[PDB]
Image: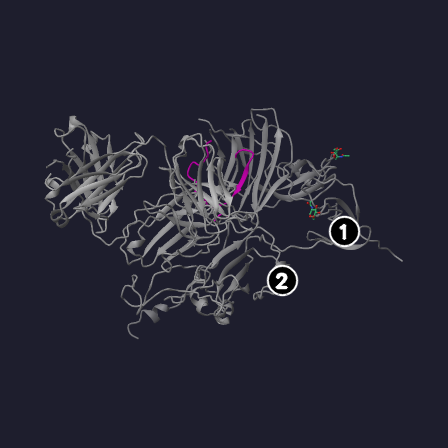
Amino acid sequence: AYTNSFTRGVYYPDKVFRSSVLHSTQDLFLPFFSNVTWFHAIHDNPVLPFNDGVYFASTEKSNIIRGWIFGTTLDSKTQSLLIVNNATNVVIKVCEFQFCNDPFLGVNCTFEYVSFKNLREFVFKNIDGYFKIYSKHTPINLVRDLPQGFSALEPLVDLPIGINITRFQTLLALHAAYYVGYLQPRTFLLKYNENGTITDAVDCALDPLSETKCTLKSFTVEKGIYQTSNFRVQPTESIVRFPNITNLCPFGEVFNATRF
Amino acid sequence: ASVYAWNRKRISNCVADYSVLYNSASFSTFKCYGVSPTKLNDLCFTNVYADSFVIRGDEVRQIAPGQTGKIADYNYKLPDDFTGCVIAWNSNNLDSKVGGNYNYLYRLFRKSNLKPFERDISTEIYQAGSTPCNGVEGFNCYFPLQSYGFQPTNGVGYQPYRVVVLSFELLHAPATVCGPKKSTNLVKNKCVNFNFNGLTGTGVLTESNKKFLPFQQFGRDIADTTDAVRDPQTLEILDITPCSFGGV
Amino acid sequence: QVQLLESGGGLVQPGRSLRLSCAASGFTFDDYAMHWVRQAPGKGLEWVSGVSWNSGTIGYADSVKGRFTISRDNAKNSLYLHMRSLRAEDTALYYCAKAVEMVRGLGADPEYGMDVWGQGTTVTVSSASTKGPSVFPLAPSSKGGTAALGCLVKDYFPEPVTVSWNSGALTSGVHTFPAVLQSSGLYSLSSVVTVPSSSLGTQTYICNVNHKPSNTKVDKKVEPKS
Amino acid sequence: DIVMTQSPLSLPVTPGEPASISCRSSQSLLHSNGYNYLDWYLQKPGQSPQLLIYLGSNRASGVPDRFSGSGSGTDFTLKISRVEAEDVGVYYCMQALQTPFTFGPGTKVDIKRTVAAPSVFIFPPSDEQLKSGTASVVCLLNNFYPREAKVQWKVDNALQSGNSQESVTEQDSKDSTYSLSSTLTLSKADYEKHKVYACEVTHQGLSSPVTKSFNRGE
Ligand SMILES: *[C@@H]1O[C@H](CO)[C@@H](O)[C@H](O)[C@H]1NC(C)=O
Ligand SMILES: *[C@@H]1O[C@H](CO)[C@@H](O)[C@H](O)[C@H]1NC(C)=O
C-alpha cells in the first residue's frame, strides 16, 4: 500500500510568463521521492483526511473513477463539495445534501455547473476561499505502478466557494488503482523553457547537491567547495535558579488572631 | 406579492449593472440611503437582497433605514443600521380593480415586534386575553388581516405603490457581483498610461510575437519588470517599453 | 425524484379553521407557480386557488371569497393553505399541484401548466360523532329462475366501511352502488348480486360490513321474507 | 364567473374514427400576440392525472402528437386521430388568461360495446329490515348500455320525486355493462298510508316506458 512518487506534483503556481530562465519559488508542493498511499477497490475506497493540499493520481482504462466528495463532516449538516462526471456531463455542486457512510451511484444550494492508458494527475487545494484544481492527462503504456517521467500540471479551475475542507472521498460507479499524497511547504527551482513551459525542477530540501543548486541559483554546478548554509545547536530546557527564601512575613498574626 | 408576504430574494454570481436604475426617470423614486447611489455601480458587493411588495401611499416613506411605522413595526422590521436603497413607483394603473383590488392583505396587530429581515405568517385570530380566539372574533379577539381597498376614489394616502428595497453586503468570503466597467480604445506607439486588469504602468506598447500558454496573462523579466501583456478584450501579445529618457 | 408530501390530515367541524401543508422533493420550489385544485366526487376538476412563482397570490374563488388564504415558504420549500371559518358546504378533497414552465421562457411570466399530482387526504367537513353501520336485507324479486338480492348499508360515519359478500367465496356479479350523503346528514349505499336457481334459497347469505375507525364488524345474514 | 363547457359529455369511440370533443368558452382564447392561452388535460382512470396540450398548439412532453386542440376564439375541438387501447380517460380544457381559472367538464371516453336492454326487478324490504321501521323498496336495472337510464316512482298515482336515491355502478369491463338502483327509502308514515308502488323505466333500448307495479301485501 506504499510506493514511490519520483518526480510528480509540479504545477504552475501563477499565470505569469517567463522564457528560458531558472526561477526559484517557495510554495506548497509534493516533496520528491516520497511515499504515497496506493489503493485498490476490489475484494473498497475508504475516506481519507484532507490537508493543506492533496495530490491525486489515476491510471485507468474504464473511466470508472468519476467522483469526489469534499467536506468536514459529510453528514449534510455542513456545506460539502461534489464533483461528478457521469456521461459527457461534468457537474460541480456545493449544496448540503445527504452523504451516507457508503455513497455512490449505480447505473441552500449556492453554486452549480453542468457541461492502462489514461494517466490523470490532479492537484486540489484551496486558499483565501478559492478552490484551485489543477489537472493533467497523459497517454501511458504501463500497468504496474506510477512510472518515472516529468510533466507540469497546468491549472484548470478556480472557484470562489469559501468552504472549509477536512476530509474527502472518491466515488466509483457500478452498473481501480488510485494514488494519493499530501503536500508540504517547500522551495523549488523551476526551469522555464522558450515557450514558457516548465520542463524541469529541483527541490533543495533533499540532499547537499540540490541545496547548492538553490544556493548558486544555477542548475549545474562545477567542481569545488561551496559554503551553503549555517548550523546552530538549540537549547533543550529552561533553568531559573534563585536564592532560597529565608525571610517570611507573619500573616499568621493578622489572620489567626484570638480576637479582632 | 402582498405586504405581509413580502418576498425576499438574493442575487449572486453576476455583474450588477445598476445603469437602468440611475437613468430611471419614469419611475418616481430611486433613493439609496446607505451609500451614494450614483457611485455604486463602480463598486462591488458580496450579495444583494431584494424585497418586493405593493403598499399604501402613506407607507412609501415608512420603509426606510431607521424609520418605523405601522408596516415598519408589524410587517417589515428594518434595522437601524441598515445600508440599502429603496425603489418606489405608483402602480394605481394595475393594482386597482374596478370594484377594488382585494388580493392584498396586511396585518397591523401583533403582540410582539418581529425580528429584522424575517417573514412570519402566523394567521391566528389574535388572542388578547385568556379566552381562546379559535375563530371567535370581536372583543379581545381581533381579525388579523385587513384587505387593501385599492380604488381610484381613494386618496393619495391610500394609493397602491410598488416598492422594492435592496440591501448590499460585502462579507469575509470573496465577492462575486462586481460592477461592469468600460474599456477605452487601444493605442499603439505612444508613451501612454495603461491599466490592464488592475496591473498598471506607463510606456509605449507595440505588437509582439511571443507565444502564451492559453491560461497565461502577464509576462515578466529577470528583475521583476513586466515586459509583455495579453490584451483582455481580443487576445494578442504586446511588448511594453518605458518611453525614452536620457541626459542632456 | 419528485415527491409531493401533503400534511394536515384530521377531522374538522364547520365553523372552525383548517390548515394544509405542501412539501416538494426533486425540484426547486421557487421556479414554478404552485396551484390548488379540488375535485369533489361526481364532479370534475375545478381550480380553487393558485400562487405564482413570485409567491404572488392570484385571488380567491367566487364561492368562498373572503375566507380562504394561500401562502408560500421559499425558505423551507413549503406551502401553507389556511381555511378561515369553514362551512359544511365547503366539503371536498383538496389537491396541490406544481407548474412546469422554465423561468424566463418569454411574453409573460411562466406560471401555468400543472402536471404533477399526488393525492390529498380524508378531509370531511362535518360536526358529527362516530356512528356504526346498519346492514339491511333486500330480498329478491317475486317474479322463478334467476333473481337478484342484496344488502343496503346505511347510517355509517366516517368513511369508509368495507362491504364484502360471503367473505369472498362468491364474488362474481356484485354491483356495489356508491355511498351518498343523504339530506338527513347520513350515508347509504347498496350492493346487489344476481343468483340462479342453484343458489336462490338454500345458499347462506352473509354480507360483511367492517368499519375499522370504529372497530364495528357486522356479519349480517340475509333472510328473504315475504 | 367564466364558464367553459365540453360537448358531448360522453361519446363512444372505436379505432377507425377520431375522438373529437368541443370546448366552448366565454373569452377570446387567441391572444393578440400570435399566441394562444388554452390548455388541455387528461385523466387516466386509476392513475395520477396528466396533461394533454400546452396553449392549444404547443405540444406537450410525454404525450402523443395526435392530440390537437384547434380552433379560434371560444370554439375549440380536441381531436385525437390515432387512439391506442389505453386512451380510455377523462378530459378537461382549462383557460390560462384570468381569474377565476375555469376547468371544462371532465368528459369520460370509455370502451364502446353493443346496446343491451336492462332487466328490471323490484325488491320490498324483508322482516329483518321491516322491523327497523324503515321501508326500502328497490327498483333494479341490470346490464344496460349506455350509461343513461331513467327510473321514476309512482305511489297511488301520486308521483314522488326526490325521496328515492338513484345510484349507478361503474362500467364492469367483464361485460362492460351498468347496474342502476332506485332505492326508495321511506319511513312508516309514507309506507302505511300509501298503497301502490310503480317503478317506471325508460331506456334507450326500450322504445316505450315499462311500468312494474304492485300493491301492498306482497
Ligand atoms: C516553442 O514551441 C515550438 C513548437 O513549434 C518549439 O520549437 C519550442 O518548444 C519552442 N521554440 C523554440 C525555438 O525553442
Ligand atoms: C468581447 O465583447 C466584444 C463586443 O462584441 C466582442 O467584439 C469581442 O469579440 C468579445 N471578446 C471575446 C474574447 O469574446
**Circle 1 residues within 10 Å: few <14, some 14–19, many ≥20:** few
Task: Quadrant for residue D127, please give it.
Answer: top left
x%, y% of residue B207?
Answer: 79, 45
Say which element carries label 1.
Answer: loop
Please tell me whether mark 1 or mark 2 is closer to you in this view.
2
Q: Nearer the viewer, residue A40 or B8?
A: B8
Q: Nearer the viewer, residue B208 or B155?
A: B155
Q: Residue at x 61, y 62 (%)?
A: B24
Which residue, given by chain and number where applicable, does mark 1 sit on? Answer: B186
Instruction: Find out whether the residues at labels 1 and 2 contact each other: C-beta distance under 8 Å.
Output: no
Which residue, given by chain and number where applicable, does mark 2 sit on? Answer: B22
The amino acid at mark 2 is Tyr
Q: Which label belongs to residue A50?
A: none
Q: Is residue B34 left or right of residue C201?
A: right
x%, y% of residue B157?
Answer: 49, 71
Q: Residue at x 42, y 66 (%)?
A: B74
Q: CA distance from mark 1 to mark 2?
A: 28 Å
Quick check: is the Cβ at mark 1 less than 8 Å away from ligand 2?
A: no
Is residue A168 on the magenta stretch?
no
Q: Residue at x 13, y 50 (%)?
A: D189
> How is the structure coloured here?
one colour
x%, y% of residue B231?
Answer: 73, 47
Q: Earlier in the sequence, mark 1 or mark 2?
A: 2
> Is C69 located above or below residue C174 in the figure?
below
Q: Is residue D153 visible?
A: yes
In the image, which residues are magenta?
Answer: A86-109
Q: Is residue A241 visible?
A: no
Say which element carries label 2.
Answer: helix
x%, y% of residue D110?
Answer: 37, 35
Q: Quadrant of the C terminus of chain A?
A: bottom left
> Is D38 located above or below residue B8 in the figure?
above
Q: Is residue A108 left or right of residue A16?
A: left
